[PDB]
Length: 522
Ligand SMILES: [Fe+2]
Ligand SMILES: [O-]
Image (cartoon, rainbow, N blue to C red):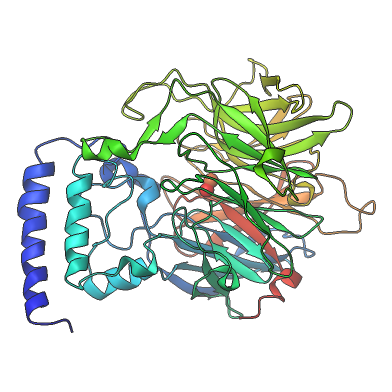
């Protein structure tokens, strides 16, 4: 229960939101297919209510009994159908977890991460927090921001606890499953012993983490250190680098001064150095006082990759290498080529001739690239991994987790091939550029293949590709959703698990070992 003044404020604010902000500022102008929910949400992209744990899911084929863990997958799932204006990325975070051990699928569960934002929107039964891309990047964006801060002025909303949406991927670090938020602190999620998922709360690393960090921090296989970047779009140092030890101890911040505020979705790691991608997509907040998006692509700016020693004391140790006209949203892997002293970076990029309208137009390519950096000389190299015969769109993917920052010959990646739909996944030979596809079959689509390495006793440390791929699939002429189990080495289906409900499309997934799960403690 609110007030009597403020109860009557909220009433009037709602009426204003609808009769003015919506009806005057918004409804008379169309809605780009990139903020239009009928597009963004349509089909299997559409959200799904929580399934509390369902046990002994029906399995065909033979799940290898040695496999023992949880496959967990984050993604966007707007609790309430959004009032106009919404991009696929804007939605509430939801995790799907499937317990696997002894040839069994012990439990499927799916749950929202209980974000300060959702907790408040549940209270009212309505969206109230503005959509970041779909509302705030629009022309009404400023008005929308005012409507919110007006409501917040009447104690009707509280941004004070962060307004992140925790939908952009997961890591398992020092016994905690963390739900990654682009513009907020991580949320701690407890994988429950019954198979369920409970949101512990908003995680700042024991007092240490004060700002928002990027949603792709990298965990070194050897050191157990978790390496992170944070960018602040406002104050002087627009980019920090720091890490955490297994002791959960935080390093001193290494400031990376940049000329302007650069958006940085992802970065990469090597044995001894971090690889930061400084690209052309940039923050010009000015734009928003005009009808414009604050996220601009700066044609003028020169794309580059910084190489910085992991235990650096000062920014002066950073080595900037120009790679003109390259943007990559994700960097699968990077490694130190000892034979050259070069740094090899494997990711997937687009070479933008693009203008202002970022998406309402045509021809979006996204190409698996080998980028070679030679820090001392500053000259670089950029080639497509696949020959122009079997050039195929290869989206979100993974390299063997244990070989992170070391040289890997195989990558596994989404075959986005009726563009945004994923018809399969491919095993890639990053040296030779050969591939084999696993076709999902007619009318069936997925996303991020999760490679699980058969933890050990093969050679001694196993062969690079002695593992398994786990992907959710989704049948059209739709029955339910399955999770396949494919043998990474001979790229062959072995087990097929049916999920009770429907697993909607998602973002980054991860695999927690059984014995990894043991450390949980919360
Ligand atoms: Fe990502
Ligand atoms: O992400």
